[PDB]
Length: 105
Ligand SMILES: [Cu+]
Image 1 (cartoon, rainbow, N blue to C red):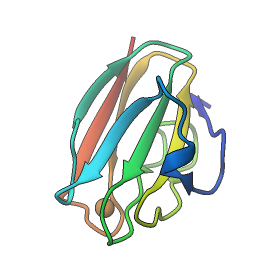
Image 2 (cartoon, protein in one colour; image 1 turned 120 degrees about the vertical axis):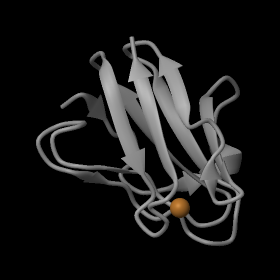
Image 3 (tube, protein in one colour; image 1 turned 60 degrees about the vertical axis):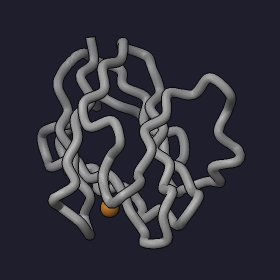
């Protein structure tokens, strides 16, 4: 694939390491809708709100299958490690007007 998944299910925001590359989900949006990272970097999304949110990459983007991330509860996190350069668009499954991309260089 173009990314590996450190944790298949969400984990506590408070457990996210200092230094992590974090995208906040707040105000019903990805607060960094265009993020540029380097190959090998891990991106961590953190849901700051009460409604559950995820990240969802359609098939062919991160790999053959869609990556429909797990629903993060408030103050939960979810990470992806990008292993190949590319431009990877995603959206929130419950709230698909919220869209983002990770550009991996
Ligand atoms: Cu969402």
